[PDB]
Image (tube, rainbow over all chains, first blue to last red; front, side):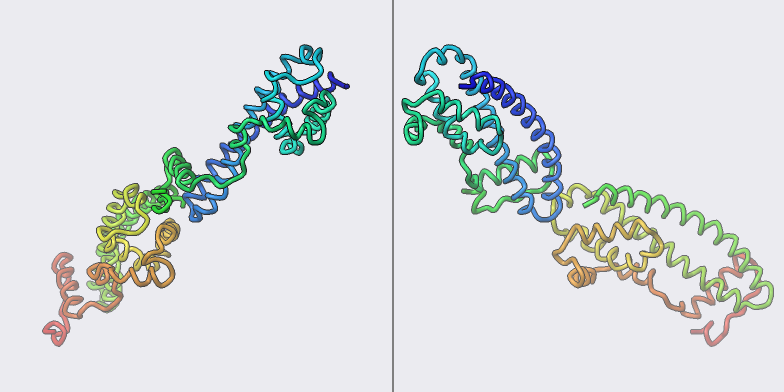
Length: 181
Length: 181
């Protein structure tokens, strides 16, 4: 298969990973001053949704870094496992997590479309329609938490609002039922 | 809200308070020599209207000093009550008097427009359209007298004319019905 198209794809993935990380950092700083505005100005719940979007983004940041490590370590053993024909256990975790998150990351990046195709084009043993679904069970559970879509515990969203109000110097009063939870 | 725009507004309020106090003092001295002229020259009633304007101005002077104390003491607890979210009783008198006199002082100063907006933007508990009207009932009654628009008792306007005629050495004869009243 097109393994150097795959490789330069990965390189662009890494480049855009860095770029998107940086851009989202920038706008996240602006948005944190903005959240200081919303919290300072009335609807802390509006700021609560804003910071929900932000903590979502931060889950994405952490997941981005984890998978950046994964694509880079897979890139290390390009020719080596390319000599092989099945995936090894040393890359089974990375491959499983990547295969699992790839559909979640299909939209975020178009290179990864080809990267996943070439992955599945690379293997059939524990690879394919369901065989790939069988081998993908070794996905990183930590990334899974960093890729879980949920409301954080309102004690923790309150703590994010508290540490924001700390860092950004607004008055925040958590809901004591949740501030105790 | 814009609490440092509010703060520098207050600073300009204080500056112009001092400035206007000084300017009105100057022209009031000139106008007192002028009132000595009118009293000396014929229409003491013309001088009576002039000194009515002046004693009005002096009510404004006294009110200015009272509220200058009020804005400065509120300025002392800027960050403190800013940490709070409702007005305290320690500032309830000042706030009520200020809220009450602010419409009377809307015209005198444009900063105070914002100061009153930010005040109402600061609070809703006993604040707002009528809730602010409810909490404003604690206005200074002494300032209220210094902000009451009325004719002074003609024994007292006669006494102002008498002590002017004393200080400015004109002949003044009060209306004995009022000079006895």
